[PDB]
């Protein structure tokens, strides 16, 4: 298939306001690269969006949604 450089991307579904404690702010309509995941829900990714400084912190996965980077054309609305 393909194996080189590709991490787990997540699409923000709800804006978030990182407190500060190694937290990362999430914005609706942005992209983040999952680097670390916790069994609590806090995920440590890096905002893959233009930013003064590479955004990286711990944020709730409940604010983002996995883009399921492992599929071949989400089937469903078949044609024939």
Image (cartoon, rainbow, N blue to C red):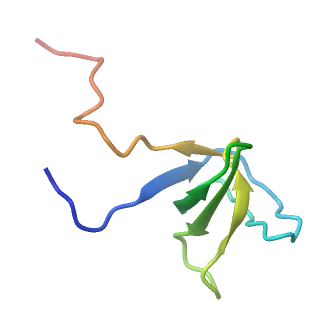
Can see residue 30?
Answer: no
x 33%, y 62%: residue: 6
Residue 5: x %, y % from top left: 30, 68
Q: Position of residue 51 (x, y in %)?
A: 61, 81
Instruction: Say left or right for 9 vs 25.
Output: left
Label tally: 0
Quarter of the picture holding the C terminus:
top left
Image quadrant assignment for residue 40: top right
Residue positioned 78% across, 66% down in the render: 23
67 w.r.t. 26: above or below: above
Residue at 64% in and 76% down: 55
Residue 75 position within the rendered picture, expressed as x and y whole percent measured from the top left? 27, 23
**In the image, is 65 to the left or to the right of 3?**
right
Q: Is residue 25 visible?
A: yes
Residue 45 position within the rendered picture, expressed as x and y whole percent measured from the top left: 59, 64
Which residue ends up furthest to the top in the rendered image? 80
Identify the residue at image location x=71%, y=44%: 41
Front-most of 56 and 53? 56
Using the image, determine if residue 66 lies above or below residue 74.
below
Residue 69 or residue 30, whichever sits in front: 69
When the figure is inspected, residue 4 is found, relative to residue 40, above or below; the finding is below
Question: Which quarter of the picture shows residue 68?
Answer: top left
């Amino acid at each position: 298939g393909s194996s080189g450089s590709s991490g787990e991307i997540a699409q923000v579904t709800s804006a978030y306001v990182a407190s500060g404690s190694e937290q990362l702010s999430l914005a609706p309509g942005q992209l983040i690269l999952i680097l670390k995941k916790n069994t609590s829900g806090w995920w440590q990714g890096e905002l893959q969006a233009r930013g003064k400084k590479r955004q990286k912190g711990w944020f709730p996965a409940s604010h983002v949604k996995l883009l399921g980077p492992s599929s071949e054309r989400a089937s469903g609305p078949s044609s024939g």
